[PDB]
Length: 335
Length: 33
Ligand SMILES: CN(C)[C@@H]1C(O)=C(C(N)=O)C(=O)[C@@]2(O)C(O)=C3C(=O)c4c(O)cccc4[C@@](C)(O)[C@H]3C[C@@H]12
Ligand SMILES: Nc1nc2c(ncn2[C@@H]2O[C@H](COP(=O)(O)OP(=O)(O)O)[C@@H](O)[C@H]2O)c(=O)[nH]1
Ligand SMILES: [Mg+2]
Ligand code: NA
Ligand code: NA
Ligand code: NA
Image (cartoon, rainbow over all chains, first blue to last red; front, side):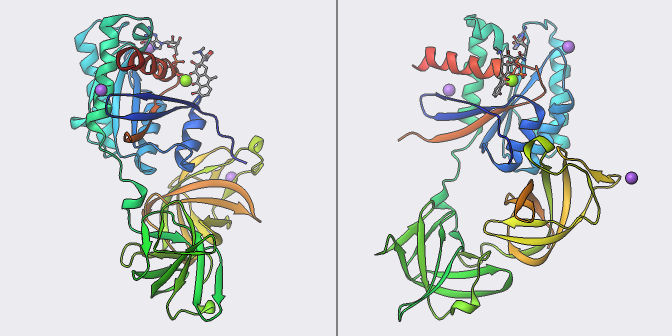
């Protein structure tokens, strides 16, 4: 099992409540960013003015882009140690160039020069820089799109045939909302079919609609139990398409996490667990990469035997006989 | 009521992510408590 090491704190600005996550070491940042163990609507990139950008500075920006972190604000730290406006502008420039190298808008990125330590000590000059950072959290990061406002999507778990009412599929609304009368496409594994929602049920009782986060049953028109299966998803028509090949960032569990004990090479054929089911696939390692050690994280191009409904940001587990040995996130659909 | 937003600190080890994390918490509490 993946070991998740985190530090959670919450704080408020007059207009917003923030759920902040901080991690100990680089491996924690990799794991937690790929698995979605903390979803960042925005990340605060801390760069010590004394060191300037360092290896994990680059890797976290790179990971951030690959896993979908939409915004990055920079807090140039330890400025209490650096009194040289020119040195500070040098570092800032280095940071903007780095952000741009990975498609973040370096030029438009807020960069606050501060000292977390002296601010923490009660020094008013520095506390002001913290307030400035919080201002950018408020102004630079837009109100995130709530689950209910996204197009409907429900990972199908079970498939029932019901006495005279019709075919029923169950699962948790991952997002959006489904109402009786709305159309729905059944995507993945087979050719996309279409149908109509003639009823949403929850706790035995008939409802008008199902909502993100709720476990419901969806009665479908005309479709028969044999035409639908686990791994497929119900979605507002035209919002998600099935794909077989994609680029992804994956983290391979370490030995201590109960993962593999040896590296795997090209030709490794594991199962990719997407939402509800396993699907075998073939892998392509990045140029120059010959093996993947337990604990490593790499960009991996995957080709599934059977299609799956997916879009950038979709999480998946890599497994060996039902046992998890890796975690990944779709970075880019290829087709 | 209030909009909820998820954020976090990324960056190289020892650059001050944990210190910044505490600093944000204490300063916002003393300013907007
Ligand atoms: C008191 N001082 C501030 C702490 C410390 O002694 C540290 C150290 N290297 O000795 C930290 O790195 C320390 O400053 C630090 O950075 C810590 C962490 O990053 C985390 C995070 O993010 C999540 C869970 C646990 C930890 C932690 C226990 O390693 C934190 C300890 C922090
Ligand atoms: N001078 C100075 N030291 C700082 C500042 N912020 C953090 N430090 C020190 O840098 C070291 C590492 O800080 P820490 O928060 O643990 O870094 P982290 O590994 O990124 O979480 C500690 O000794 C801190 O006291 C700062 O603004 N100024
Ligand atoms: Mg830390
Ligand atoms: Na240094
Ligand atoms: Na603010
Ligand atoms: Na070899």
